[PDB]
Image (tube, rainbow over all chains, first blue to last red; front, side):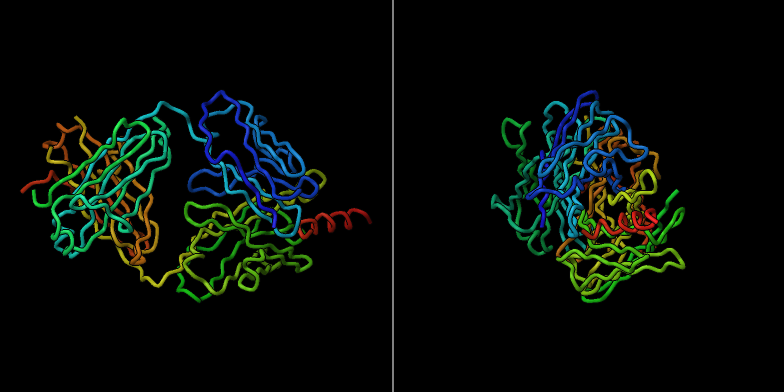
Length: 214
Length: 223
Length: 16
């Protein structure tokens, strides 16, 4: 099976700059049978380039494709705001077609620390027998962030889930929500609930906490 | 203009089978390759297989050999994907795609035309509306508040604020799949602290699969 | 290569 490896994973650029995305195959792709697709959140992929360098119909002239053998490129000569998306390569030079894992183009901006908020479970939820503690990391850049939960100063594991918004189209930031799930029994058992946040924008970790019942 | 129109979202139990249709219009049908590609939530594209209708020739990804069957009905210009042995690993949006056509009618092999996508959810869970709990603003000049949309199934839900009048500062997060098999998501908004005594904030939740519409007023925390 | 089948159909039809 031909494995396609795209690089970089994520690219931070600005409109007006040139973007070069790369796609490397684990073995030679036969006859330049390599295509490039664009995908925006919630949409079907869109074909940009076929057969290494053929520009698909209706694709702007600023997109071009190049390469041979095991090394292929997609170049955007001058980015526009609508070019920030995910890009996939695909080989179809043998019967078992494969796709790369994708490269995302994000808009670059200055490092921004998250503003952190913690939310106790509501009395409404508690009267239903379950407890969710929520930690919100709002409007930060870059995307990488770390949330640690502590209950009575003890580090929690395996009982949280998180997700991250798409990059904001106006201010280039990301936001993250983490939920700590416990039984109502366990929530009433303990007192101190804390979310500790580390991020490149922070000179020291930020801890938002509350005491249950205050 | 070549258009591909797929059938609607599917909910299936594990080890059952699913059939997804793709109806083509706006060109020739039988002499072009049709393919199926899927995308699990937040993940990469994965090719499943294809068919050339004229010669009844199919080609499947080896990791699905035996589980995936593709067929075509020339009289209705429709191509079908059948997948058996479903598990939660098969929850994904499934796309049909057809190869492009170049100069002199030459087929282009790469996938120029795409269907709108078909969500297939594979789970033991039963369809269920969300509970909507408030994320009340901190009792302590920007305040964050929100709604927790919990324990619904399947995707999707929509959230607005104040019937769509409030859009600035809103972040509605991707849902997570909990170990219960049910989804949960949060939607938050940052507003001026001084508005908390005077302005009303209401999250409007719509879960179309269960026909559940909920409005939740989020009020400052108090005891 | 299965992805070449429709090109052979196109070639064979255009040929004669």
